[PDB]
Structure formats: structure tokens, C-alpha cells
Image (tube, coloured by chain):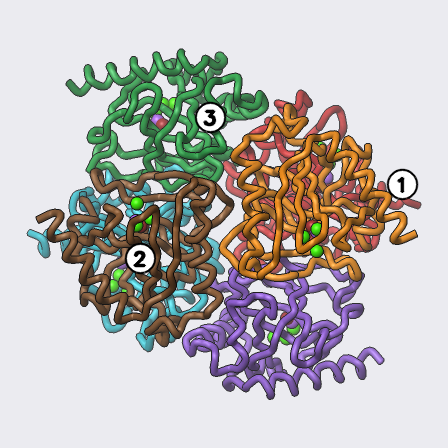
Chain colours: A purple, B orange, C red, D brown, E green, F cyan
């Protein structure tokens, strides 16, 4: 099947969403769900020796300003495999402009890892961890000559509002 | 496609079955085949720092008392990736009650790893290895507050009889 | 879906082909795409403690003399996951007879890893690396009692001609 | 040299101690510093498929009731290699009796990972993580037939007092 | 210190020997103990994509016909780190001539992994595993142009006799 | 022993030097040889999700402007373990100022990996790989607030001249 089109955005939107993971934490390979076939594709290898600091993927049945599904970052202790579904609780949102496009990213934790039970908003995350994620997105494209701007972080409510917006952008694009 | 519904239970049932692996040996993440979409899903992260001692999954087109496909444990030297099909020879069966449900698990070896050619019954397995598997299932849910009981091990013939039962439970559930 | 039948051979054939990876570099497990279901299958475990020196897979919508899709070897620094699509530039071809069947294999590099930008023909590859790949295929089946013969390497143009041949063998087999 | 005898307990005892790591997080092999030669030794393989949830080792120039150097658990994101020195801040202590011996264990974070800058006492640690560590020590010896009892957790000040005690036990044993 | 010269051959020679591991199972890098400094050294990278099928190292205070300490192969489930001491029970011996030198290798299991408790002689090892080890040593130097000959396997008593011989060769060389 | 002080700079200086590796490629942990004890120490965890693109360490019996042994980067396919000695051929040098100190770094390949036999000067390295290494050093300290400047790359002869300089700086510092 095609996970992007055929999975709902979540079981309890926007408190709990599905994250379909494309890139496990620790990868330098930039995998993406091929929206046409539903297969994993290598988009590129990052040009710098950086690794994804989070399990990285999409919320199904969403769309966004960069012409792709809405980006989601899930904090996993043990990374998952590509194309794994995780039930995720949004706790904040990274505000990023990428090559002139709004490209904000939900920050979420797995509902079903009790380690994260007390992570519910952006203030629960170690500051240095937010900084490491922002810095990755600030510099990972530098050798590609693409401009990114990290504006800061929003809280869980702002993240949830943006999830609802992305869900509507999908309905409008794909009727 | 949906591997659970669209794959036969095996090529030479019950001497050789297909094992569709959900969890590679060494994982703490409890992956499962999502029976609705056919995608891998993170059910939960184990609450304790334990890892699956076997490649763990299901026999396709089976059903069982816990309301899931029949559980199978494949002894792999190098773990496979989730959603890999392995041709497996049943050699025994772990007798487990889980939260009040019968939830026995086939123990099998890969037909096409010659390392295991002389493993054909439960007496061929190192005792300490059977004990390690049983102990994992005895304690892995303890922090979840769920009761499990490991009653012992049955031999290859008992395992094969249970495989035939599970194949019939599927036909009856899904007509 | 079924990647073998439903993916085109490439976006710019034969300069750029799709490689659907079955076996990540470093694996001893011989995974293959199950042509019937589209799932990954463990064909066997290699009988010797050897590992695949390349990310190994197939070109979609091709066929070959051994009754399988055309084999492709992609040089990846970080191995991909099974069933990942890579856009690959053919740079040469390994000439192999396997159990009496022609079973040549394209050698390719990822288009979107800039590390390999200057790899465009067989003369760009370290000699010892070509030798290591050939030796793997010379000896990996020795304990299986199967005869293989490595005849040498052809250049990028010869590889591209063989890709076109394999594309035609598929059209003829599957009408 | 011999790290146990020739390294000081820490640079700013008891606020900052040296942890000499024996077992990286994720290991099932129970490595220990051989107090005679200073080499790493495999004491045993754990009898169950459990892994160390922390980087595990000793504080140099300490001694304890079980006739070994004082145990320390360092929370590392990326595990270190055996025999690595880490500057560690004690934040709490696990109260354990092991086979009739007091065998409490310092819980510490690396000073020089900014991720942990705000971890300073036992209340800063996710409850489920404390539970996972305690459960590991509650059950990891069960198949060895050895009795352990986990009594609970003490805070950073109690941990620091115990570090000072262990430093004195060493001076007395080794004059 | 220098592990080769300053560690005894074993705690209960020849029933239990110390194996000082140089190369973890799964490595392609050919590490060796530098007999001069006691540090690990990269001797070479194997010329073929083969990996050590066993944890590989030496028995301390031994010497052998190839002008090196006596080779020992320890069957570990989880590989150890280089320079780890393992208490090992010899169960057999691989008979190998290497570049004209006798270079037999003890096959052993860890005393303190209960998985191997019933492995006590060469007949306890899966035939395919013995074949995989022999084949590795038959072919791993082929691209280096060095001749090796594998003559077969001896039993535990023959292995123990050879351990005693190697212990004496050391005493004579190093007085 | 103490590898920094007790190992010679190389077997054929400056054509072949010893590299004592501190940090395997792929690590985010910044390990260093503790010059006092000879043990591995965690200096810090990098503040960003970057990994060392090379096996990273020192040339023994050298000194440099930043008050440390001369830095060396060895291109290894399979990373080594910390404190491994590699015989390395210098092929170039990265020109870096770090926090106001000259802190150039030799780029080298392992003599005994035939894959690199034709790598002998800076022009043999893929441009994108040089760029990835430079970019790592340009940005890896950015969150630490430390200024680095990468000025470019010198060739093998310039690297060899700098190795001779560093060897002399050591003799003068340590008499
Ligand atoms: Br994304
Ligand atoms: Br299951
Ligand atoms: Br193939
Ligand atoms: Br300890
Ligand atoms: Br050896
Ligand atoms: Br350095
Ligand atoms: Ca995009
Ligand atoms: Ca983007
Ligand atoms: Ca995006
Ligand atoms: Ca269930
Ligand atoms: Ca169950
Ligand atoms: Ca079940
Ligand atoms: Ca075939
Ligand atoms: Ca073939
Ligand atoms: Ca083929
Ligand atoms: Ca003890
Ligand atoms: Ca204890
Ligand atoms: Ca203890
Ligand atoms: Ca030798
Ligand atoms: Ca030899
Ligand atoms: Ca030898
Ligand atoms: Ca420095
Ligand atoms: Ca520096
Ligand atoms: Ca430096
Ligand atoms: Na995306
Ligand atoms: Na199940
Ligand atoms: Na194939
Ligand atoms: Na201890
Ligand atoms: Na040796
Ligand atoms: Na340095």
C-alpha cells in the first residue's frame, strides 16, 4: 500500500499522531518515502558527516509549504526501522525556513515508551538537545549551498495547531 | 500487500513454515505487523533493558487465543530485518500463558542455514538457551504489571500439532 | 506493491538506473526480493563467514539468463536498508558465469553521494576493490558445491549495453 | 598501568568523580577490570537476554562491602569503550543488597555532555528509567540462583556520602 | 603491562586457558597484540570481504612454529573487545599449515557462558560451523598470494597436548 | 605503558608514521589519550549530532602549537578500536587554526589496506570528502562558541615537513 495516502494522520489528532519514520536516528543517508510507489528511496547522502539526531519522518495525510508531507521528529532511544509507524505525542515545533519555504517540524515523543511519560511540552526537553537539533538543520545543507533559517521553537499547543493546518493542506491538495 | 493475510502458512506445512519476522534478535523495541495496513508498527518499547533473544514474528494465515497470529521464534545467527520471510523448521514449542490467554510460541530454525542442520527437536537446543528464552518471557512484562506463566517446553511434534490448530483458527476467524 | 514489476528500470536509462537493494553491504544473510509477494525473503545464509562487499540488488523490470532480474552492485559508504531505491550510475560490469548461467553484474555508484562524483568508469575504481568483489563471487558458493567463474570486468559502455539487453529480456518474458 | 590503583577517585571529589567504565550500555557480556593485571576480563555472559542499561564501571581507589571497587553507573547517550575514563557527576544512588553484601551503586551523568547539564539529583531522572535499572538488578542474576534486593534510591547527597565512605574503605584495605 | 609475557597461560592448564582476544568476531581488520609494546596494532585489512568467524587471539606465555604466540579461536555469541581476557575450555584444534609453517589453532568455548556448557569436544560443534572456519582460513589469504592448507580437525585431547607443547616452546624461546 | 611517550613516531618517518587512534570513525564521543596515565578518556561529547569522518588520533612522540600531540586523520573503511596503532602513509594536511592556535592535521591512509594503494597525494582524494572533513572542523565547535578557521589543504610533501616539525617540538618540550 501507500502509507502516505492510506494511513490516517493519527488515532487522536492532534494529541496523538502517527509518525511514519523515514530516517532512523544515527543515519547519514537521507531516506524518504517515495510518494508514488510507497517504497523507501535514498534521496541523497548528506554532504557532511552529520547524522539525524531524531527518528525522522512524516505525518500521513498531511501536506506542507515545501510540497511534501509535514515533517515530524520523534525522540527514540533505540531507533526504529524505516517505514515503521510510531504513535507520537507532539511536545513542540521547530520553526525553520528552508530554501525560502516554511518547513517547520513537529517534535514528538513515543506514547508507548514510559521513559518519556513526563515529556509533554517544549520546556521538558534538555536545552542542549533542542540546540543540537536546530544546529543540525542550520548546517546540514551548507555544502549543498541551500539557505536555511532556524527561528526558534514553539510549544506543544503551537505544534498541534500546525498539525491541524497540515491535515487541511492535504485534503485541499488531494481533494 | 498484507503479508499476514496473503502469504500461505508455509511451503511444506507443518514441517516447514514461513516465519514473517517482526522483531530482529537484539531489539528492545516491540515491533508488530499492523494487521490492518501491513506496515511495521512500534507497539511499545519494553519497559526493562531486555532484548529479544530470537528473531520474533508470526506464521502467516494463523490465529491464536490471544487474538493475534501464532507467535514464532526463529534462531538466527545474524538477525534479519523486520518483514523478512524465513523458511523455518519447527523444533519445539514454549508453553506460555499470557494475561490469562494461551500464548504458546513455536521455536524454529532456518532451513537454509546449514549451521542448524542437526537441530530437529527440542533436545538439540542448549538447555541454557531454552532457559534464557523462558526467563525473558517470564519477566519482560513485570514492569507492565501483566502476569505471565511459563509452563515448559514441548517437542517438535507438539509444535507441529499446534501449528495445524492455529492454521484452522485463522480459517474460522476469517472464513 | 511489487517493486520488481511496478518500478521502471530507471529515470534516465541506461545512464541512471534504479537499484532496488536486497542486501546491505556487510550482510551474511542472502536476502532477495520475493518476486511473487514483493516482500523481502531470506534465500539462505552464506555458508562461509563472508559479507556482501556492496549494496546488492536488482534493476526493476529487467530479466537475465539465470532466470532472475539483472543483478546490480551499488557502492554505498553507509549501507541502505533492504527494499531501498537508489538512483545509480553504472560504471562497469563484472563478468561472471554462475552454475552454467551468464550472471553478469552491473557495478554502479549512487548519483546523489558527491563522494563518488568522479567515479564514471571502471578505471576509477581501486584495483583491490574490484579484486575483493570478484574474489567474493569466486568463493562464496564454494561450500555449496556450485561452480562460478569470474572472467573479468567490462567498462561503463559495456555495462550500459547489458542493461539495455536485460530490459528487453524482461519485456519478452512478461510481455 | 593499573587504573584501579593508580588513578585518583576524582578531580573534585565527591562532586565530580572518575568513572572507569567496564561495560558499555547495550552489552550482555559482563566485563570487569582485572584488579591484578589491569586488563579487561570477561567475568561471565549474563544468563538472560538482558543488557546493561548504563555505562557501568568503578570509581578508582575505592573499595566496598562486596570485596570490589565501588560500582558506578554513568548515563551515556553514545556508549563508551571499556577502560574509558569519564568525569562524572553523582546524582543519586541505587540501594542494593547482593548475595548478602551491601552493593549500592552511584548513578551519575557525564559532566561534559551538555544534554545532562540540568541533571543534578535523583528527581531529575525519568521514573521509568530508574525502574528499568532497578529491575535489571532485581532479575539479571535470577538464573544464577543469586538473591538480590533493591531497596530504593537515595539522592545526590547520600550518593556523595557513600563515595567518601568507599574512598576510605580503599585506604584502609590497601594501606 | 604486556599481556603476552605477564599473564599465565591459564588458571587450570590445559583444561582451562586464558584467551587474550585480538580480533572480535565480525571484524575484517586483522588486529594483533604488538608483542613489543602490548598495544593493539592493525596488522592489515583482509584483502577480501571476509570476517573473523570467531573471537580470535592468543594464549599468553605460548609460542609456536610461525614465530608467534599460539592461536586460539573462542566461540562467543556477543563478541568481546580487543585485549579482553576470556577463560576458555579447549574443545578441539584446527590443523593448518600456513606459508610452510605449522599454525594450528585451538578451538575453545567460554567457560562462563552457560550456552556452551555441553560443548566439550569437537563432535559437539555443528559440522557446517567447522567447515565455515576452515574455509575462512583456506581462502582469506588467497589475494595475498600465500599458501594455506587445512588438514582437518583434532579433538579436545589433541588440542590440550598442543597447548602444553606451545607453553614449552615459550619457556625455551624466552628462557 | 604510555603510548604517547614510549612509541616512536613511525617506522619510516615521514613516509610511514604510526597513528595511535583515539576516536573511531562514526563516533560522536570525543575520546583522547590521557597523556598522564595512557588510558582513554572521554574529553567531551560533541555538542552537535556530528560524527568523526575519519579514524582520528595522534602521532606518538610529537607535539604541536595547541599543546597536544600532532593530530592525524586516517582513512579507514572499517573503523578501528581506540588505542589501536596503524601504519599510515601521509598524503596531505588540513590547514586549521583552532581557538587561535595552529592545529593542522595530517591526512593519511593505512599502508596495509590495499584499497588505498593508489592514494599517495592530496589530489587522489575525492573533493567532496576533503570538503566533508573541512566542514566538520569548521562547524563541530560552533555550539561551544570556539572559533575555527579552515584555510585549505596542503599536499603530501607539506604534510611530511610538518610531521618533521612536530617530532622536533616533542624533543624540545620533553627534552
Ligand atoms: Br520528512
Ligand atoms: Br508475535
Ligand atoms: Br540480485
Ligand atoms: Br562494577
Ligand atoms: Br593470533
Ligand atoms: Br587528536
Ligand atoms: Ca523536501
Ligand atoms: Ca526541508
Ligand atoms: Ca519538509
Ligand atoms: Ca498480543
Ligand atoms: Ca503475548
Ligand atoms: Ca501472541
Ligand atoms: Ca538466482
Ligand atoms: Ca547468481
Ligand atoms: Ca543473478
Ligand atoms: Ca563482585
Ligand atoms: Ca554485585
Ligand atoms: Ca559491586
Ligand atoms: Ca603470524
Ligand atoms: Ca598464520
Ligand atoms: Ca599464528
Ligand atoms: Ca586540544
Ligand atoms: Ca583542536
Ligand atoms: Ca590538536
Ligand atoms: Na519530509
Ligand atoms: Na505476536
Ligand atoms: Na539477483
Ligand atoms: Na563492580
Ligand atoms: Na596469532
Ligand atoms: Na589531538
Q: Secondary structure at mark 2?
A: loop
Mark 2: C-beta under 8 Å from nearest atom of ligand 18: no
| Disc number for residue C173 | 1
The chain to which mark 2 is attached is: D
Q: Which residue is mark 3?
A: E141
Q: How many marks?
A: 3
Q: Which residue is mark 2?
A: D104
Ligand 30 positioned in quadrant: bottom left
Q: Position of residue E128 (x, y in %)?
A: 59, 23
- Which residue is at a point 36% across and 15% down the rendered structure image? E160
Q: Position of residue E121 (x, y in %)?
A: 47, 18
Q: Looking at this view, is D12 or E45 the one in front?
A: D12
Is residue D115 toward the left or the right of residue E119 in the image?
left
Q: Looking at this view, is D169 or D116 the one in front?
A: D169
- Which residue is at a point 34% across and 73% down the rendered structure image? D121
User: How much space separates mark 1 and mark 2, taking CA atoms?
Assistant: 70 Å
Label 1 neighbour load within 10 Å: few <14, some 14-19, many 20+: few
Amino acid at each position: 500500500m501507500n502509507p502516505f495516502h492510506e494511513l490516517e494522520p493519527g488515532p487522536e489528532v492532534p494529541e496523538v499522531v502517527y509518525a511514519l519514520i523515514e530516517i532512523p536516528k544515527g543515519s547519514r543517508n537521507k531516506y524518504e518515502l517515495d510518494k508514488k510507489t510507497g517504497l523507501l528511496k535514498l534521496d541523497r547522502v548528506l554532504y557532511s558527516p552529520f547524522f539525524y539526531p531524531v527518528d525522522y519522518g512524516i505525518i500521513p495525510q498531511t501536506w506542507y509549504d515545501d510540497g511534501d508531507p509535514f515533517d515530524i521528529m520523534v525522540i527514540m532511544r533505540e531507533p526504529v526501522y524505516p517505514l515503521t509507524i510510531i504513535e507520537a505525542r507532539p511536545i513542540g515545533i521547530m520553526k525553520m525556513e528552508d530554501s525560502g519555504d516554511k518547513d517547520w517540524k513537529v517534535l514528538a515523543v513515543p506514547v508507548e515508551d514510559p521513559y518519556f511519560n513526563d515529556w509533554k511540552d517544549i520546556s521538558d526537553v534538555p536545552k542542549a538537545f533542542l540546540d543540537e537539533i536546530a544546529h543540525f538543520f542550520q548546517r546540514y545543507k551548507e555544502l549543498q549551498g541551500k539557505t536555511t533559517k532556524i527561528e526558534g521553537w514553539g510549544n506543544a499547543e503551537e505544534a498541534k495547531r500546525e498539525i491541524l493546518r497540515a491535515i487541511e493542506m492535504y485534503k485541499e491538495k488531494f481533494g
